[PDB]
């Protein structure tokens, strides 16, 4: 069933707020994947060997590196492993400059434990490099996501870390294939959306603390599930996010139990990209972007992470995400997909205007 442990999501939730605060339409990203990226710079940084460690607190596992590696390796494999019911891949890669001598063992670390690689490109040619990064993005998302950077976004870069994510998943309980109705966006008149409607047994409650309805829709495979947080009429997404912290969400999700529910949801199909450097500095991770920031365990002796990118695609429709109480989500909502056997926040997103 639903996850019964304590979600290690102090960072995850904080970071989703930063992103969501600063974006006026649909957003979709992967907290868990950002913690991988941050953990890779960490292993590359000198402070691990034996300020950056203090700032990478809620991402690094109790200052002992073998635990950090098996924690992330186990959580990556829990979600990514081959199965009948869903496909999920979390692809990650350092695009390092020709001139840099990459340490081969760092390569091995990244490959084995974090499921990531390192690959030489020449930034002297922006047009080549952008095409090599954008093609890689396609080749590890079965061409669902095809472009993540432009030559312009690689200005004066030395090392560029990219994260993408892909996910195919089938609802345990499909919606009948039928129905356009209004959607009440926060800014501007009601836009029309195509909805899907069904009634069934789902985990549900109306959170008084959060001021929102919450709905869990499981995917086939006893591992993944999509949760929806739908603000009451009297409050916005912003106001709910303020009310969300590790503990209040834990408790909101804890209170949920199986009811009959009348589920009305808007179909949507959209992806999203962002530069992590800015929203990372805002939440506290500064030291790795400073003029000192070194990568001596990644690059042979200094250099730093020029830029970091993440992109994710998501869909909901009658069959899934592939590419009586009434929970009628015809206004902006929040959503996340998690590994229900581990607590992992694999996706987190937000609907402001659903197009399909």
Image (cartoon, rainbow, N blue to C red):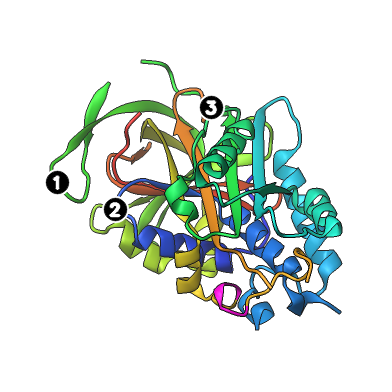
Q: Is residue 321 magenta?
A: no
Kind of element beneath mark 2: loop
Residue 249: percent from left, percent from top: 50, 62
Residue 258: percent from left, percent from top: 53, 42
Residue 19: percent from left, percent from top: 42, 60
Picture layout, residue 290 above or below residue 40? below
In the figure, residue 72 lies in which quadrant? Answer: bottom right
> Which of disc 3 and disc 2 is earlier in sequence?
2
For disc 3, the marked residue is 322
> Which of disc 1 and disc 3 is earlier in sequence?
1
Q: Is residue 290 magenta?
A: yes
In the image: residue 260, left or right of residue 354: right
Over which residues does the magenta segment extend?
288-292
Give yes or no for contact between labels 2 and 3 (Cβ–Cβ under 8 Å).
no
For disc 2, the marked residue is 24
- The residues tagged by marks 2 and 1 sit, at their Cα atoms, a distance apart of 12 Å
Q: Residues within 10 Å of mark 2 (few under 14, many from 20)?
A: few
């Amino acid at each position: 069933g639903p996850f019964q442990g304590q979600r290690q999501n102090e960072f995850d939730l904080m970071f989703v707020k930063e992103i969501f605060k600063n974006h006026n339409s649909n957003v979709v990203l992967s907290p868990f994947s950002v913690k991988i990226l941050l953990t890779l710079i960490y292993e590359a940084s000198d402070t691990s060997f034996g300020n950056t460690k203090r700032e990478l607190s809620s991402v690094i596992q109790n200052d002992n590196i073998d635990h950090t590696r098996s924690y992330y390796k186990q959580l990556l494999e829990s979600a990514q492993q081959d199965n009948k019911d869903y496909d999920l891949n979390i692809a990650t890669n350092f695009f390092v400059d020709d001139f840099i001598e990459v340490i081969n063992k760092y390569q091995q670390i990244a490959n084995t434990h974090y499921h990531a690689m390192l690959e030489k490109v020449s930034y002297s040619n922006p047009t080549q490099t952008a095409a090599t990064i954008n093609n890689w993005v396609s080749e590890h998302t079965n061409g669902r996501l095809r472009e993540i950077v432009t030559p312009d976004s690689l200005e004066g870069a030395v090392i560029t870390l990219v994260n993408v994510i892909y996910f195919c998943g089938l609802w345990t309980y499909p919606f009948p294939e039928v129905n356009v109705k209004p959607f009440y966006g926060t800014r501007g008149k009601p836009t029309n959306a195509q909805y899907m409607e069904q009634n069934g047994q789902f985990y549900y409650d109306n959170s008084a603390d959060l001021g929102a309805q919450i709905l869990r829709l499981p995917y086939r495979g006893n591992k993944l599930a999509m949760y929806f947080i739908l603000p009451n009429p009297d409050n916005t997404v912003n106001q709910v996010l303020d009310r969300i912290n590790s503990a209040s969400l834990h408790q909101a999700l804890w209170y949920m139990e199986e009811n009959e529910v009348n589920v009305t949801l808007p179909k949507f199909k959209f992806d999203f990209s962002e530069q992590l450097n800015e929203p990372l500095q805002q939440v506290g991770i500064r030291e790795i972007f400073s003029q000192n920031a070194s990568l001596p365990l990644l690059a042979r002796g200094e250099v730093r992470v020029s830029r970091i990118f993440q992109k994710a695609g998501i869909t909901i429709n009658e069959l899934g995400s592939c590419a009586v109480q009434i929970f009628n989500a015809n206004r902006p909502f929040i959503f996340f997909i998690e590994d229900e056997t581990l607590g992992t926040m694999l996706f987190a997103g937000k609907i402001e205007n659903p197009v399909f």
